[PDB]
Amino acid sequence: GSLKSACVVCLSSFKSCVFLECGHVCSCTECYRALPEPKKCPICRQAITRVIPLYNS
Ligand SMILES: [Zn+2]
Ligand SMILES: [Zn+2]
Image (cartoon, rainbow, N blue to C red; front, top):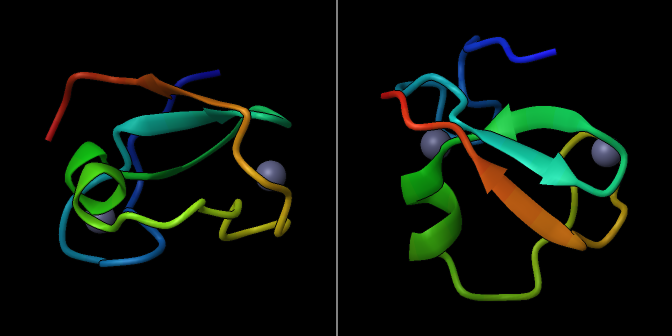
């Protein structure tokens, strides 16, 4: 379920965020909270309904 591969957006930090939409785990907390927009799932383009942060790097 959880995994910590490379954050697909930055590619520097691991992914530390499961996007509660579809269960895609792909972003990192800092990427999310830093960028303010309504963010879309980087993999599937669904709007994010909630973010379940994983406290990792
Ligand atoms: Zn990131
Ligand atoms: Zn998705």
